[PDB]
Length: 61
Length: 61
Length: 61
Length: 61
Image 1 (tube, chains in turn blue, red, cyan, orange):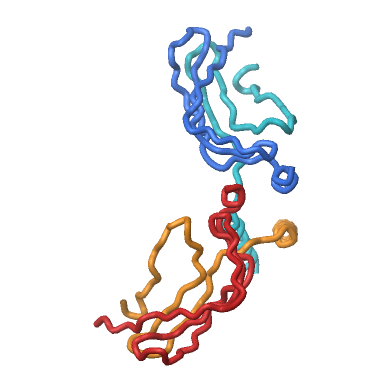
Image 2: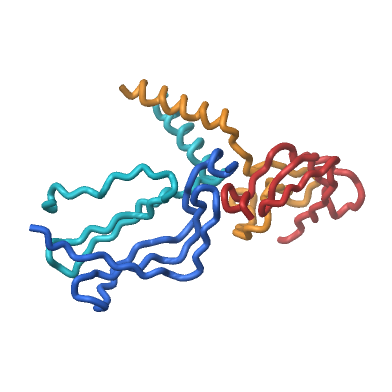
């Protein structure tokens, strides 16, 4: 509560975005989020390793 | 940990440097560091009185 | 939307911290990743900003 | 080094807070003491900096 009321949510380091295009599925594009640390809502969020996420491809016409 | 992540190391007050030249030894110059307060690696460092330090004289040719 | 007019979604949820945006090209494996994460400013950084302000007003004078 | 080229030692250890530098003249009791300690900036100081920025942009206009 004190941290959020003083400074709000902010990043400390890391959490860079990189595209890889891994072929897990032809209808998705893989994205890698690099390891980092941040304080969200006053709670620390330390991730030691990168997280992989995938976005669906755009087909709307 | 939280303080160092949010703000790093910083000084609050005090810790001024003053040269006195006290003759404790002919090969040294005495320097006085005034009392002060600081946060190093998040840990408070509160000193009530000054500290005397000495630097060796320069003789390199 | 078309690439000239596409914009990221607008959000105001306090519970989430935005790390960046990922743009996917229309019907392609390529994707553009940019990081817009809010990052802290330590006391040294703020002092450097203050020095920059001092230089700015000096140049103004 | 000679007085025209002498510089303080370079350090990047996070565990230490630099309070200042002491310069000793070649073969003399005299010494020059300067404080370069990183110091905090209270929210009042940051508001004053913001006001100074406001004045700078007003003068630019």
